[PDB]
Image 1 (cartoon, rainbow, N blue to C red):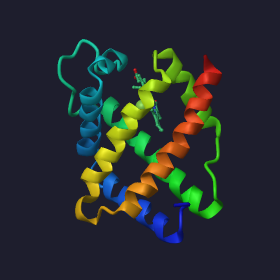
Image 2: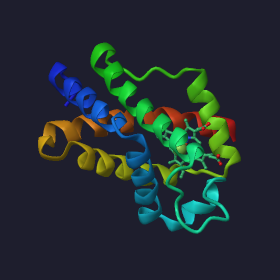
Image 3: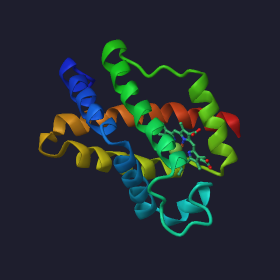
Image 4: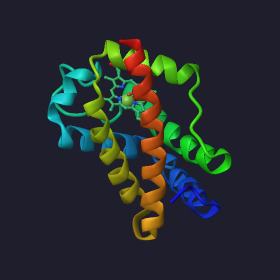
Amino acid sequence: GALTESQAALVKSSWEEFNANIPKHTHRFFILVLEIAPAAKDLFSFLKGTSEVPQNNPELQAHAGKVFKLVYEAAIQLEVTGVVVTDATLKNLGSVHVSKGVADAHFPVVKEAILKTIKEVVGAKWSEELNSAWTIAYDELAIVIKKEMDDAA
Ligand code: HEM
Ligand SMILES: [F-]
């Protein structure tokens, strides 16, 4: 699909819609994760020793917000520039995943959890053109982090 001026316009628009409700979209996102893979729970400090996914845990919200922002920034960068740029942050990201016991096969878990989360976020405006656009942007960003984990291990 490439990332036409028209496709980028579509991701920006849909991320603005996501940020618009962090405590919801982020707790949803963690539930979609634990649905696709239950075992994932022991990983998260703020999920350990608990039984259910905490709903007002600042640690949890701050965490999940950061995740989506990063995927959107990635899509704009693709339309303007044609690429996703690797910086200090993406590199430190790779380190912390590894400390915490996260692997590659965990990534389609968090992807589907994000496509499903955005399909839920944009509702009837959903188009093939839009699905195509977030898919392109995640894929392109995951490619970059997975790269940095391998390097932190
Ligand atoms: C493009 C996709 C992804 C992005 C942009 C991303 C981003 C991040 C960021 C920014 C942090 C640190 C947050 C903080 O300091 O507060 C973090 C921590 C973490 N992430 Fe990810 N992530 C991605 C995929 C994944 C996957 C697939 C898993 C595995 C299930 C995972 C598991 C974790 C864990 C266990 C921590 C440590 C949390 C702690 O115990 O406090 N992430 N991630
Ligand atoms: F994460």
